[PDB]
Image (tube, coloured by chain):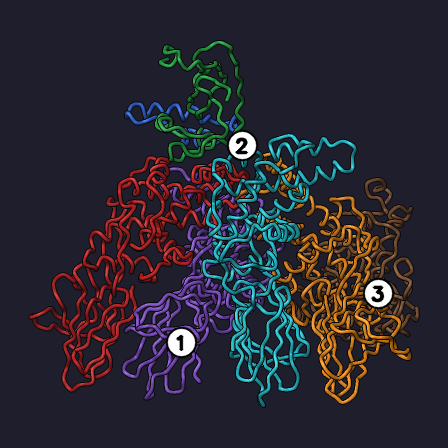
Chain colours: A brown, B orange, C cyan, D red, E purple, F green, G blue
Amino acid sequence: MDVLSKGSLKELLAHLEKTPLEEAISYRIGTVPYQNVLISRNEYYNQLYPDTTSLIDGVSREGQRNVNGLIMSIISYVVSGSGHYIPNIGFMLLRRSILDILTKHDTGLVTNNLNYGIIARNLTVSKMNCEQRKRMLICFKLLAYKDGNQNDYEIYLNQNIPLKQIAPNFIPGDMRTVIHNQDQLAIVGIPAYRLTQSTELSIRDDNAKSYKLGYVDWYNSNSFLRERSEFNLIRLKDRDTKYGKLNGW
Amino acid sequence: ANRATSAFLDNPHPVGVNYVDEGSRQFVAVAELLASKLIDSSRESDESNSDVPFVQAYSKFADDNPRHLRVKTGGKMANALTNVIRSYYSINAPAIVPQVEIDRLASKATVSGDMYNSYAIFNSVPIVEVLSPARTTVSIVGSDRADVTMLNTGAGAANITFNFGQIAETVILKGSVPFQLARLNQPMPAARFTYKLRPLDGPFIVVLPVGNPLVISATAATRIQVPLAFNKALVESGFQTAMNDGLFDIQNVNYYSSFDEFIISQYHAQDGINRVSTCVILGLALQAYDQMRRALPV
Amino acid sequence: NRATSAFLDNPHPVGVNYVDEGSRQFVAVAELLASKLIDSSRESDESNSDVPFVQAYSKFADDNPRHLRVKTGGKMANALTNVIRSYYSINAPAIVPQVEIDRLASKATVSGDMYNSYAIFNSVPIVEVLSPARTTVSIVGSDRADVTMLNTGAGAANITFNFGQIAETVILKGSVPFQLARLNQPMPAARFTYKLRPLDGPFIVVLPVGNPLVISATAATRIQVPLAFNKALVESGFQTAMNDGLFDIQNVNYYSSFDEFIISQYHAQDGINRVSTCVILGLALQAYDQMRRALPV
Amino acid sequence: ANRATSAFLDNPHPVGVNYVDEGSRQFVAVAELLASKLIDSSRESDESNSDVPFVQAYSKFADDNPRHLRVKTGGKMANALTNVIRSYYSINAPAIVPQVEIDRLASKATVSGDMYNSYAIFNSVPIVEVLSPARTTVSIVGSDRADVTMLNTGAGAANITFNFGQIAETVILKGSVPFQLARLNQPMPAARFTYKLRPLDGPFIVVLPVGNPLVISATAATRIQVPLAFNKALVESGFQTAMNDGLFDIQNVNYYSSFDEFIISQYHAQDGINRVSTCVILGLALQAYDQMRRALPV
Amino acid sequence: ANRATSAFLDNPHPVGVNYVDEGSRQFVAVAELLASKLIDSSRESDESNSDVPFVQAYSKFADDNPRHLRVKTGGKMANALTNVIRSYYSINAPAIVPQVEIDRLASKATVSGDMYNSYAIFNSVPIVEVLSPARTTVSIVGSDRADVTMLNTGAGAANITFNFGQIAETVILKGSVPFQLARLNQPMPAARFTYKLRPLDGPFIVVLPVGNPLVISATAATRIQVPLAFNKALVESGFQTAMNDGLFDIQNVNYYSSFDEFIISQYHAQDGINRVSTCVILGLALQAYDQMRRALPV
Amino acid sequence: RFGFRDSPFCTSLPRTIMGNDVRRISYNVFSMMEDIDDVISEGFILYDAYFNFSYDIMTTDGVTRLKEDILIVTDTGNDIKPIHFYIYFENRNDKKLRYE
Amino acid sequence: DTSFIDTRKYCTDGLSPREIQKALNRQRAYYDRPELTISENKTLLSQSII
C-alpha cells in the first residue's frame, strides 16, 4: 500500500532505502503460482468465475528458493504490494534494504546470470499496466548497473518496442537524474473518478481495488501525514527538503 | 466418422486483460457519451448558422479548441480511445495508455461504468460439431444463418448428431423438406418443417433419408449482459472501421466478419465467461470509436 | 471458365442533372425538414394537441393541414419525388425547374457538405473467379458471398480470386480449412479464415479432389457521405421508392438494396463520378422515407 | 548507318490554344500571388495563436468563409486552376471554364500578366541525331545529363556525327578518356577531356578509336523567357503533383519526367516559338497549383 | 532465375522510438523557427553597425549572452537538437535528453508542432525486383534516375518482369530505343519510347529483342505527409552535415546518399507507415540543424 | 401580386437573369473589394450576413425609393447603409411617375 | 476590431500603426501613387497584436 502510493522516482527510491527485505517476503504459504482455478464472484454471476492465478497479485504465492525467486519477490512487492514465500532466508539478507539488495555488492547474492526475458515472462508482463511495467524496468536497470550488464538491459529494451518508449530515464548512480524525472508511478492514489465499493472479476483487478479503497481509508486516517498542516511537527530527517540525497549516488 | 464445425468458432485468440477496472470502464462510458454529443452538435450547428455548438463539444472532447489550420483529430481522447481498443483485442498488444491519463479523462463526465445493467440478443449460430457416418457428406456454411447441407449416398438411412453447445438459449431449425429430429434416447417425431430446441437438453439425432439432399437452416439467440448505452447497430459499424483502420492488425490473432461472431466465439472457449466481459467493453469502445471517427475522419 | 457477381453486371448510367451546389442544398434541406416532420408527428401522437405537427407540415408544405383534404406534402414532396426519379437513370426526364428548387432550398440553412463523413458498405465485389478444366464454380449472394467449388479432375486445381480494387478489407471463411496465397507466393498451411486486402492482387486457392469447398466472403467499403447519412433509413427509402414505381424506367438495372446499387456503380468505369450522384440519391431517399411514413398516400 | 535520338525529344504533342489572351495570363498571375499568400498566412497563423490570417487568405482565394464542417477545397479558383492546367497540356482538352469566370478571378489583384520580364536556365540535352558507321553501336541515356556510350568493332577508326540542334546555347562534353572532336571540314585537335561547343556552329565529328568504349557525358543550358515570379523548384514539384493528380491523363499525348524536358521538347518542334509561349504560362499555373495544394491538401 | 534489386532498398535498419510525442514535436518545430530567426538576425547585424539584433536572437536560442573570446556553440538548445538527431536515426542510439529539458526549450516559441498538414514529393525510384530468364543479364544503377541495362544473349526474345512496389504513385519509363511494355495478361502494344505507369496496376513485362542492349530510365514520384515548414533543400544539406559531423556513426546501421533514399527505403519496410512518421520528424530536425550550424559553426 | 410600383420583393432571389448568372459575393469579401463601382454596373448578390430592413406601405401612388444611399466606403472597408423602403401602390397609367 | 472574422487583440502599446499608415499614405501622395488599399490597410493595422 505504501509502496504503491509512491508517485515520483525520488519517493519510490527513498522508500526502497528505508524498507528492509523482510517486507518483500510474506511468510505465508500461499498456493501454486500458475494454476487454472474457479472462483466465486456472486455480484455478477451465479456460475463460478474461471481465472488463472499469477505471481503479480496481492496474495502470497510459492516461490523458488534461488536468487531468481528473491528478485521476483522484490519486483512483485513493488508492482503488486505483496511478495512471495521463500523459506529460510538468512537474517543478514532480511535486515538489508531492498535498494541494497538490488544495487550493492556487499550482499552475497550473485545475479550476473539473470535473464531479463525469463523474469518478465514469469512475472507476467502482458498482464501488467503501464505504471507496473515502469516500476519493473526500474528494478531491471538497478540490477544491470550493479552487475555491469548494461548492454543486456539495452538488448532487452530493443527487442520490445513498447517497453523502450516507456522506460524510465535515470542513471542509477547520479541523483541529479532522479530529481529531473517527471514519470508518474502511482498505482494507488486519490481517484479523480468516482470509486465505489463494488467487487471486480479478475483476481488482479479485485485485489488492486482492495488496495485502492484501503489507501482512501488510509488517506483519511490519523496515520496519514499532512505536510501543509503539520510540517513543523515532522522530524528533520523526514521533512521534505530540496537537498535530500540517497546514500551514495 | 466425419466431424464438421463452424468456421468462426475455431481457435479463439486470448483477449486483453487491461483497462477492465472501474476507472477504465468509466473512461469508455465517458467517451461514448461525449462522442454522442459530438455527432448531435452537427445537427445543432445546422439549426443555426454558427459552428459554436460544434466548437463547444470538440473542446470538451479534445481539451483543445478546433483550428482551421489542421485536421480535427480528437486530441488526447482520440489517442487514448484508439490505443485502448488495440489492447482489448489481443494480450500481445501493449497497454500504452497510463492510468493517470484515463483517470483524468474519466472525470469529464459523471457517468457510472456499470456494464451489467442490460442485455442484448446475439444471432450467431454456434455449431460445435456435426458428426456423420462414412457415406454421408455434411457441409456447414454461414454464421448468422447456418445452412447445413447433408447428402446420403448409402443404401440405408443415416443418423447425424448435432451439437449446438451449452451457451445458446434457443435454436430454431428449418428444413427444405420435412425431417425428423429427436434428442438422444427419445422416440423420433413425425416429419416437420420447423423444430425449436434448447441446446442444454442434449445432442440431437437427425435421420437422413436416401435420395435428394436435405438442407437445414439454423438461427440462434443468445442473451449477453451489456451496458444500457449499448447500440448494436453502432457497435457493428465501429468494428468494421477498426478492422479497416488496422486497429486489429497484430500477430497471432483471429479475424471475424462481425462483432456477433467475435463475442460468440470467445464465449465458446474453454473459459469463455471471463472473455465476454472484456468483449462487451470493447463493443462500447467501438461504439464510441464509430461516432467519433464519423464526426472527425482522418 | 469465368464467374462474376450478379449485381456487378452492367451498371446503368445515373442522372447528370440536379448535382450542383444549389441542388445539393435542396436535398439537405429536405432531409432536415422531413426529420422534423416525423419527430413532430410522434410528439403529436403522444400528446393531446396537434400543434407540433401543424407547424412542421406548414414549413414543409407551405400550407396548413386540413381535415377534408389529404396531406400530400406540398410542393416539396412533388419536387423531391421527381428529383429522385432523375438520379436513378439518365433516361428519366429532368423536368422540375431550377428556380423552384432554389426557392425550396432557401427554407433552411445547412452547415455541411456531402464529403464530411463516411459510411461502411458491406457488399462483397467478386469481379471474376477464373476456374480451370473440370472445376464447377457458383457465386451466390451479395451481402455474404457463397462460392461453392468442386473439381472432378485427378489433380488439384488453382482458382483465381479477383475482388477488385475498391474494397478495403475482405474476410474469407471456408467450410473446411483451405490454402490461399497471393500470386507467385508460397502456399501457407490450411486455415479456416483469411483476411485480405484486395489491392494485394489476385489470390490463388487450391482445391483437393475429395469434397466440395464453400468459401464465405464479407467485405467493407468506405464511401464519403454527409454526416446526416443513416444507412437504416436509406434502406427503407430504397424499398419504398422501388414499390412506388419511381424506378420503373426503360433500359435500367434493378438492385436488391442500396448497398448493391452504390457498390456496382463504384466498380465501373467513371465510377468515382457516379458515386457522388449515388450519395446524393441516398440522402434524398432518406428524406423520402421519413416524409412518406408521416404522410402515407 | 545507325541513328540514335534522345527519348524525350520524340513526337511532342500539340499544346492547347486557349487561355492565352491577356486576361487569362492575369488570372494565372493572380492565382500565383494568392496561392503564395496562402502558404505565408498558414505560417503566420502558426507563429501566432489565431486562425484569422489563414481565414482572410482563404476568403480572398476561395470567395467563401472557412467552416469547420466543410471540405475546404479552394473554391471556384481551385476549380478554374485545375481546368486551365488541363487545357494547356493538350489540344484535346475540353477547355470548359468560360471567359466571364476568368475575368472575375483576375480582378482580385492588380498584378500584370507579363510573361517576358526575366529568364530561366533549363538544363536538358537535346541530342537530335547521332549518326554512326555500320560497325559501331551508340546508345543514349539520360535527359539532364546525357551519357552516350559508343563502341566500335571494325578495324578502322570511325567518325560519329553529333547533332545538338539550334536551340541550346552552350553544350559541355566530358569523356571517360580524352577524345578528338572537331567541326565539319576542320582539322582534328589533340585529345582532350572536356569540350565547350555552340550547337549553332554545325554538326560535330568524334573519332572513335578501336578498343575500350568511350562514354561522352553531355550537359546543356538553354535560356527561355519567363515571368519574374518564376521558381524552378516550385514548378518541378507542381509538375509532379499535377501528373500524380491525373491532370495530364488525356488520350494521344506524351508524358515527360520533368518540366525541364517538356519545355525543351516543345521548343524543338516545328512551331517552337509559339509552343514555348504557352508552356511558360503552364509553368506559372503549375507553380500556383503547387502552393495551393500544399496549403490545402485534398 | 535472376533477381535484381535497388541497392538503397536493401535491409532498412530500425529507427528510433523516442521523442515522438507531442511535447517533442513542439521542440523540433521551435528549433526550426528559432534557427531561422538566428540566420536572419545574423545577416541583419551584418548589414548594420549594431549587433543588438544578433545578441537578442542568440540569447533566446542559447539562454546565454554572446561573449567575445568564446566559441558561441549554441547553448543548451544545440546539445538537445544534436542528441535527438542521434536517437532518431536508429534505435541503438541512447536517448539521454531529459523530457524536462525538452519541454523547457519548447516553451521558447509558440508553434503547433503538426507534422501532417502538408506533403512533399520524393524522387527516389523503388525497383523492388526485376526478374529475368537465365540467358539475360540485368543491372540497376542509380536512385534518382534508375538506369536498367539488360542484354539478351539467347536466341529467342525474353520477357522480363518489372515490379515497382505499391507505395509509389507514378513511374515514368524512358528507353534508349522503343520497346514494348504490358501488364500481366494483356496484349503488347506497339513499340514506344516512353510509358507512364501506376505501380499498383501490377507487375510489368518488357520484351527483349536479340540485337542490342536496351536501357530503361525510371523516374518515380511519392507523396509523404510533412509539415508546411518542410524545405527539401535545407533538409538535404542538413542530412550531409549530420553525416559528416558524426551524428550517424553508430553500430548496425545503413547509410544513404540522400534523405529521399532514407525515407523511401524506410517506407517500403513492413512497418512502413510508423517509420515514415519518425523520419519526417528527423527531417525537420535536420533542417534546424543546418540553419543553426551555418550561423554558429564549430 | 401586391401591385407595388417598382416592387423590391422577389419570390426568390434569381440565380440567373436574362440567361446570365448573377454574381454572389460574401459580405466579408465585399468589404475588402476595391472596384465596387465596376461591380455595381452589373449587379451582385450579397449573403453571409444578416440584413435588417424596414418598410412603409403608403396608400397613395408615388415613387418607390430608399431612405438612404446603398453604399458607404471607408478606408477600413465597404458597408451597406440601413435599408428602409417607401413602397407605393401603382396605377400603371400615370405618365409622370413612370418617367420619374 | 469591428469585423466579424477578426477575433484578434490589437495592442495599444508601442508606436501605433495608424501613424505609419498616415506616413506611408503621405509618401504615396507625393509620388501620385494610389493610397493604401483596404487589404494592405488591414495588414498594417493588425501588425501589433497580443
- Point out residue D111 in the picture as x, y percentages from the top left corner: 32, 37
Q: Residues within 10 Å of mark 3 (few under 14, many from 20)?
A: some
From the image, tell me which residue sits under label 1.
E205
Q: Residues within 10 Å of mark 2 (few under 14, many from 20)?
A: some
In the rendered image of this protein, does residue D227 appear above or below residue A169?
above
- Point out residue A176 in the picture as x, y percentages from the top left corner: 67, 55
- Label 3 and label 2: CA atoms lie apart by 64 Å
Q: Is residue E216 visible?
A: yes
> The residue under label 1 is which amino acid type?
Ile
Q: Residue at x 47, y 17 (%)?
A: F4
From the image, tell me which residue sits under label 2.
G8
Give the chain letter at badge 2: G
Q: Between tags 1 and 2, which lies in front?
A: 1
Name the side, left or right, on which G26 lies relative to D273: right
- Label 1 and label 3: CA atoms lie apart by 59 Å
> Of residues C121 and D234, which is closer to you in this image?
C121
- Point out residue B86 in the picture as x, y percentages from the top left corner: 68, 61
In the rendered image of this protein, does residue B35 appear above or below residue E270?
above
> The residue under label 3 is which amino acid type?
Glu
Give the chain letter at badge 1: E
In the rendered image of this protein, does residue E160 appear above or below residue B250?
below
Name the side, left or right, on which D129 lies relative to F84: left
Is disc 3 on the same chain as disc 1? no
Q: Quadrant of the N terminus of chain D?
A: bottom left
Under circle 3, the secondary element is loop
> The residue under label 2 is which amino acid type?
Arg
Determine contact: label 3, label 2, CB under 8 Å.
no
From the image, tell me which residue sits under label 3.
B169
- Label 1 and label 2: CA atoms lie apart by 61 Å
